[PDB]
Image (tube, rainbow over all chains, first blue to last red; front, side, top):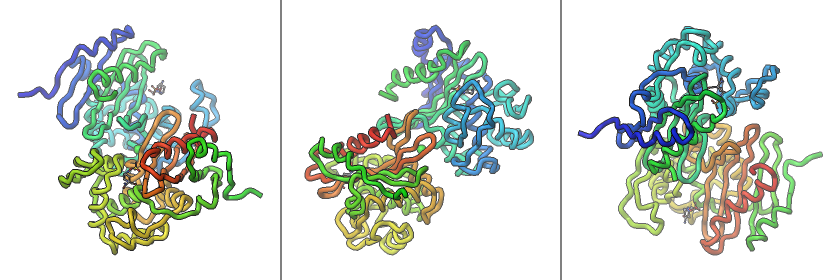
Length: 241
Length: 241
Ligand SMILES: *C(=O)N1C[C@H](NOS(=O)(=O)O)CC[C@H]1C(N)=O
Ligand SMILES: *C(=O)N1C[C@H](NOS(=O)(=O)O)CC[C@H]1C(N)=O
Ligand SMILES: [Cl-]
């Protein structure tokens, strides 16, 4: 019989081009088949870092901590290193600019008990929120693999997570990254010390390709390699032009 | 003091450059003010043509004629002149490829009584469905002006139409045309005998600009001028780069 999961090591060339190492995992929804350059690393669990703003957003919306995608979270007046964080935001722009202080406030309002219960309900990674309620996804005990990211994203795509359909549609809107006549990408980046992520999916006319990539990220320089390397894989596989 | 609507006739140069005539209407949501090159034509009511697939989609979803954006409507097997129509479609691809026969099926299932009631609820144009329920927006009596399109789109953007929030969110998803780090465009084209349309909005980080344009279209050549002329106005006004 055909293989649910196949390894394509030729994608390693896209990492080697940049003196980097990592994994891209692709899932072809119509075929129900997955593809990766590194089967072992595809299943190793890492801190989710800013990719956690996907479940954090869902939980905040479903609990009413965030009323809708237009509600304004005012800047607290603390001048931070990332200039785009030093302004008022809504859910859309907080996702777009990956505004940590806004999501820390969401997490504090959610609280430890509800956050833990909701990650259990989501089957999210190791479901472990050990650490600070407002930083465990950056320096605490939570861990998720690339294949687990795809599983979670597939549930989100199909409105199957244990939150309202409305919360799922709002977050999928907030994940919008790029759209043209050839494809739509909904995705979220992340970076914790050691590891950069890009997770999401590519919508085509007649199929959807889910993706989850992580790579060794010693420096914030080359954060753009997350999208660049993934797009080289997508181009090689003729998913995007 | 300032007016709700201001005329900017310098935009006429974008029509003149293409030996064409028409109107662009913009609405700045933050400032609650509108701008147009021709206030008279901005209020002239025309057949909506394929821009009707916005309200038609909303009504079909809210009545359950269309269950969700993934439900497939199979090709009826009749080979029509637009090749992309000769295939199966869902709501997303039917709006992208402007598949009239799919929307005619929606309209027949909606039926005349519910169609008329819903367009009245929407305050949509002249609300006149006289003719056939599956062609009145192509060759019947319904008429809508560019400013009426703006009013309708503003209600849709704010989830204020008399249909479920869910139906409104799905249609706004289906309207997605272009997205990048600078802007998102949700919009729909149309073409009836001698008139081309483009209506929708441009989402920015801290504002939304609604737009409705129409132009004289004596031949099918120059349909791309609908977006091209609109984008020249958007660029002149520094809404997009
Ligand atoms: C999340 O991983 N973070 C917040 C912010 N996002 O940048 S990224 O999404 O482009 O990775 C900066 C990196 C990281 C953090 N340092 O908290
Ligand atoms: C809608 O106005 N129509 C359907 C189709 N779409 O073309 S457009 O959306 O690019 O204007 C062809 C034109 C028109 C029609 N002939 O019914
Ligand atoms: Cl969207």
